[PDB]
Image (cartoon, rainbow, N blue to C red; front, side):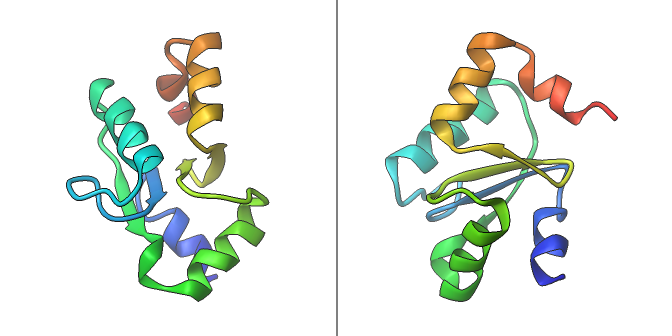
Length: 99
C-alpha cells in the first residue's frame, strides 16, 4: 500500500540513487538524462533514503537493482531495458503513458 502509493505518485516515477539534479549513480544519471531529453516530466524517489522501501521495491517490481522506472504504476525496467525499449520504439515513453 505504501509502495503502491509511492510508485503512483506521478504518471512517470523514477526510483533512483540520489535526486535528478544530484544523482548518486551513473545509471541514475543516464536515465534522468534520457527522460529529460524526451521532455518527459517525472516524479522521483531517492531509494537511498530508506532500506525498507529500497528492498521492498525490489520485491515489488521483481527487479534486482536500481534505478527503476514506473509509468502509470507499471514497472518499465532499469536503464538497459529502457534503452532496449527505445531502440524498439523511439516513442516508447509516449506509448507507455497511453491508456
